[PDB]
Structures are given as C-alpha cells and as structure tokens.
Image (cartoon, rainbow, N blue to C red):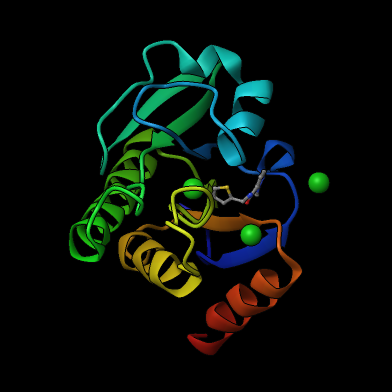
Length: 163
Ligand SMILES: Cn1nccc1C(=O)NCc1cccs1
Ligand SMILES: [Cl-]
Ligand SMILES: [Cl-]
Ligand SMILES: [Cl-]
C-alpha cells in the first residue's frame, strides 16, 4: 500500500502517467477506439491481446510487466440513465478489485463514460463519485487524469473538500 493513500488529479495524457498501472476507458471489443483508449493503444498496444470484456467489467492485460486494466464503462447513448448508472458503478468496483489483486501502490485512472460514452451529458460528478465509492477502501495512490482545464479544477475541488 501507499504510506498515506491519496487522490490527485493531473491534466495531461494518461499515456505519460507516473503510476504503477493504468486504467483504460476501454470498449467491450478490445478495439483501439478513441480518446483515452486510443492513447492507451498507442502506448501499450500489446495490452489489447484478448482485452475484450463486457460492459461493467475490468480485464487486466500486461504490457511487459506494466498492467493495463481495461475498464468498460457503459455508453449512455445505449443504456437508460438507471442501467448505465449501475454499470458505471460496477466497472469502477471491478477496477478496485484489480488494483487490489495486482498489489500496486499507485494507479492512473480516467473518468469512465465522460467522453464519447457520456451520451452528450456532463458526467464528471457521477463518474468521479463512483470512482471514489470503489477506490476509497483501496490503499493505492490514485491519480486521476483529465484533459479539460475546468474539469481539472472541479476534480481538484472535489478531492480537497473530503480531506
Ligand atoms: C487523460 N487523457 N489521456 C488521453 C486522453 C485523455 C482524456 O481524459 N480524454 C477525455 C476522456 C475521458 C474518458 C474517455 S475520453
Ligand atoms: Cl500531455
Ligand atoms: Cl468515454
Ligand atoms: Cl476531461
């Protein structure tokens, strides 16, 4: 575990993370995809060998010894708000199980279902709160990666509020 488990947020490409493993915002088919997924495909393409997994699940594949946790959030274009909310919560719970299983002291994690799977809605708070619900019982340092300057501020505020 980390000596004093923390949450942090950085506004930069998660392919440049300084953590012991990464969470991919994957598609269910293990395709290269777009946004975070495409960045992860560029950096760790070996990790997409048999990475396909259903919605609401996480599947870890090594790139060398570097774990890539493929976490499949729901596409809110296809799910009802209710069912999507349940699958988004479930994907983060599976991430917390994988992070624990791997024994890492740190993890880089994007906000699932906030990009092209958001169904055109701002889901920062929904996705971040499900992240916290899952990760709070883990002792890994969690570093959340985002690209939007306003999101960085809001994620940072949400973290510092609970400290
Ligand atoms: C941190 N990062 N590295 C590369 C691209 C991004 C990013 O956060 N993009 C927006 C998305 C959030 C979830 C799916 S796409
Ligand atoms: Cl960058
Ligand atoms: Cl997304
Ligand atoms: Cl963002």
